[PDB]
Image 1: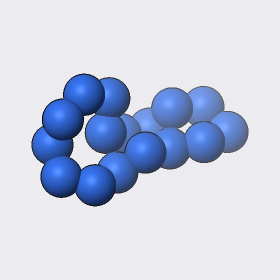
Image 2: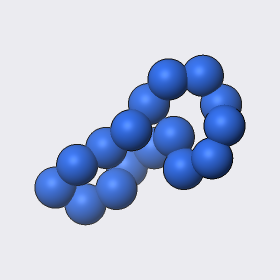
Image 3: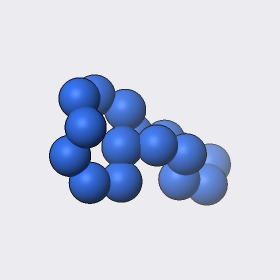
Image 4: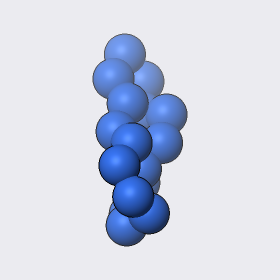
Length: 16
């Protein structure tokens, strides 16, 4: 989707 990846103390992952 967007920034679905590592992101500092937090991360977002779920379908591009």
